[PDB]
Image (tube, helix red, strand yellow):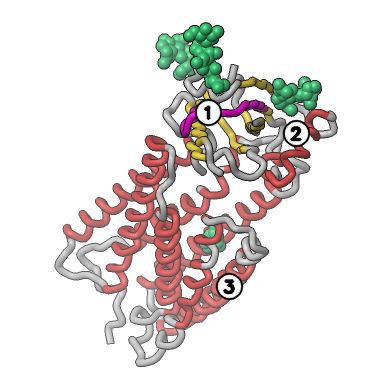
Amino acid sequence: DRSKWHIPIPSGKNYFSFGKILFRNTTIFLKFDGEPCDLSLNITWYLKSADCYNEIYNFKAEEVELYLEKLKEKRGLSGKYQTSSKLFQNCSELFKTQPLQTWQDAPYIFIVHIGISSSNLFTMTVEVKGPYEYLTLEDYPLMIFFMVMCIVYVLFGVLWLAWSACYWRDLLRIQFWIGAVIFLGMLEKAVFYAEFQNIRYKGESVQGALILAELLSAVKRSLARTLVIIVSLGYGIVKPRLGVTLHKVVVAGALYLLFSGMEGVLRVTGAQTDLASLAFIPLAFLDTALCWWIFISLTQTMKLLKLRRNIVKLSLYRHFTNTLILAVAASIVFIIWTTMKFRIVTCQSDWRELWVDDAIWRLLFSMILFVIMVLWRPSANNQRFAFSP
Ligand SMILES: *[C@@H]1O[C@H](CO)[C@@H](O[C@@H]2O[C@H](CO)[C@@H](O[C@@H]3O[C@H](CO)[C@@H](O)[C@H](O)[C@@H]3O)[C@H](O)[C@H]2NC(C)=O)[C@H](O)[C@H]1NC(C)=O
Ligand SMILES: *[C@@H]1O[C@H](CO)[C@@H](O[C@@H]2O[C@H](CO)[C@@H](O)[C@H](O)[C@H]2NC(C)=O)[C@H](O)[C@H]1NC(C)=O
Ligand SMILES: *[C@@H]1O[C@H](CO)[C@@H](O[C@@H]2O[C@H](CO)[C@@H](O)[C@H](O)[C@H]2NC(C)=O)[C@H](O)[C@H]1NC(C)=O
Ligand SMILES: O=C(O)[C@H](O)[C@@H](O)[C@H](O)[C@H](O)CO
């Protein structure tokens, strides 16, 4: 996901190709540097538009040499293209013209080939610049989304801090970890925004910002799941804090984080080593099992509360269960819709809305967290949610 390319031309077949999605009226800059010239050069560049996104996704450089001829023979795909070629005696390195600008916003495939006629000799610098300095399309909406999420989490943290300050006299231990979750979200969104700003204004992504961000996301989700499990079991809320009730159970249930650590990082550093897609299923199955456990535990706790005729906590648990069930239903609907809208079409004819699959989950999590926070608002009578032996 870069925007600048440095390449030693005397390497392999010398073909340099890239498939991306660009804005409209975006220029491409080519520069050459190196040692003096003693031989003849031939340059040939092709720029092809895309009709539907599939070709970009499955574009393999290994067969470029064939793909080019596949475009010449007309058994490729529709879409107008611009081709050009030039000759240089020895170097003519101080060259101007190398028209070559985008005419319509859509997926693009760019290919450049160099033929030498008579060891590293030259070095090619390739840049792409649109209306924004280096922020190519497919990232602008994502950057806006991350900025908005940063603002929303800042507001959430401010509200939580104000509420805690206004009722600092007495607080609940379970009520403290909300602050930790908010802090983790703050760090995650800040890292996203900083990385995106750096990429836009420099053209190169951070060395390891994505890995740290994925680790933070996994940690936050694991903490949320463990807190939900503990609240559902009623540990410290309905039943007393028994010696070994979460011991070996709740903590032993944190291995979910590990499975999250083998998915987000992988997804980020896509390697496609036959394990990229496979890591997705087991995590979903584990989450389904966790929900299966949670609902049963929550039903048992509701029965126990009904037995002893407790009123205040009964309504709170009813609201909690309603919110959780609605969240689960919404998540299932969203997953089914994404699966039936993105991975069923012959080829994706709607390339605009592919960033939604990586943003909807965060928005849903933020909404659920906000609802949960609203449920547990600190107040003067902040002791009803205690065991009270
Ligand atoms: C290496 O590349 C350069 C640039 O493509 C070749 O051009 C050299 O630079 C001059 C500058 O114009 C070329 O024009 C010549 O100008 C002289 C007057 O100074 C004129 O009498 C010639 O008829 C010609 O128009 C010229 O072609 C050439 N000159 C020199 C001294 O190199 C250059 O030829 C290339 N060198 C090799 C070895 O291929
Ligand atoms: C395409 O983008 C370029 C660069 O953003 C535009 O170039 C500017 O055009 C306006 C009006 O045409 C000028 O006032 C500016 O001076 C130009 N920029 C520079 C750096 O000179 C261009 O107008 C856009 N449209 C087309 C059709 O090229
Ligand atoms: C520079 O490279 C291009 C790409 O191969 C050459 O274009 C071909 O050149 C010969 C001329 O007959 C044949 O392979 C084809 O007819 C050309 N392809 C076309 C016209 O699409 C080009 O000739 C090279 N420049 C030279 C040789 O000066
Ligand atoms: O992989 C993802 O994009 C998300 O982490 C989802 O898995 C949610 O966490 C979840 O399944 C609902 O709780």
Q: Does label 1 point to a residue whose CB lies under 8 Å from ligand 1?
A: yes
Q: Secondary structure at mark 1?
A: loop
- Per the rendered image, the range of residues in magenta is 30-46
In this view, 265 is above or below 196 = below
| Furthest residue toward bottom | 243
Who's the residue at 84% across and 30% down the image? 73
Q: What's the residue type where badge 3 is placed?
A: Leu
How far across and down, in percent of the image, does residue 41 sit?
Answer: 62, 27
How many residues crowd mark 3 within 10 Å: few (<14), some (14–19), many (20+)? some
Is tag 2's residue or tag 1's residue first in the polypeptide sequence? Answer: 1
Q: Secondary structure at mark 2?
A: helix
151 drawn magenta: no
Q: What's the residue type where badge 2 is placed?
A: Leu
Task: Give the residue pinned by disc 3.
Answer: 286
Who's the residue at 48% across and 29% down the image? 36
How many residues crowd mark 2 within 10 Å: few (<14), some (14–19), many (20+)? few
* Nearer the observer, 381 or 180: 180
296 left or right of 209 in image: right
Q: Are marks 2 and 1 in contact (CB under 8 Å)?
A: no
Q: Quadrant of residue 117?
A: top right
* Nearer the observer, 327 or 285: 285
Q: Secondary structure at mark 3?
A: helix
Task: Give the residue pinned by disc 2.
Answer: 68
Q: Main secondary structure of the magenta part?
A: strand
**Alpha carbon distance from label 3 to label 2:** 46 Å
* Nearer the observer, 312 or 26: 26
Q: What's the residue type where badge 1 is placed?
A: Cys
In this view, 324 is above or below 254 = above
Task: Give the residue pinned by disc 1.
Answer: 37
Q: Quadrant of residue 74?
A: top right
**Alpha carbon distance from label 2 to label 1:** 29 Å
